[PDB]
Amino acid sequence: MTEYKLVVVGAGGVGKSALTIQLIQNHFVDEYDPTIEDSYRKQVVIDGETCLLDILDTAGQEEYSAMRDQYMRTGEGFLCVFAINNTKSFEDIHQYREQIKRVKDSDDVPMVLVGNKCDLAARTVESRQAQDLARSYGIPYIETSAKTRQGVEDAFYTLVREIRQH
Ligand SMILES: Nc1nc2c(ncn2[C@@H]2O[C@H](COP(=O)(O)OP(=O)(O)O)[C@@H](O)[C@H]2O)c(=O)[nH]1
Ligand SMILES: [Mg+2]
Image: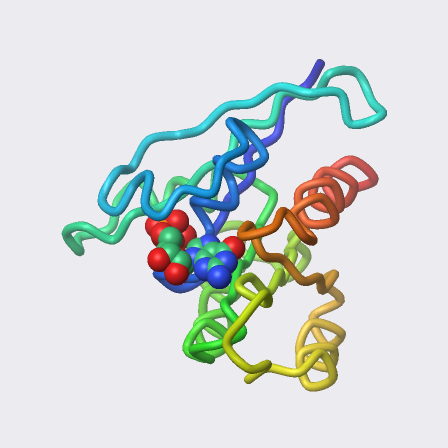
């Protein structure tokens, strides 16, 4: 069976939780955890052996840090969400990919720069400049929008595909 932890991170307001719960319960949630810090679990068979997928999401309440540090050292998959409408998510990926290298103390994670919220808000982040951002780190690039379940499949699936082959 084996199990994997989807260490998700990427700005606050990109749609990272509504995206996770979507693949699980399947339902566009406007806010199913505006301040909750619980781990989501959903087991399925991704053409393997029923690999349990324990997704991990953040919240933002308080600001002392503690489990986040031990989350980069425990989990391994990095779904770096980034909304392509506000742009602050892109600048947030340029720093969240340094602390992960801090914890593991290495530059070779199964990172995954996924752009969410591409179903609206004029494309502020085209796929060209974004293609050169992830291409430099050797990480896969994808698009996503839980508002219509578009791209959500290529994100989660490609995530377990990078951790497995690794
Ligand atoms: N258009 C669109 N907006 C989204 C999507 N996911 C999240 N959002 C926005 O983020 C809010 C949903 O709350 P939440 O799931 O907590 O967002 P997160 O905390 O940033 O992941 C909504 O008000 C949406 O405007 C998505 O797939 N499409
Ligand atoms: Mg969230």
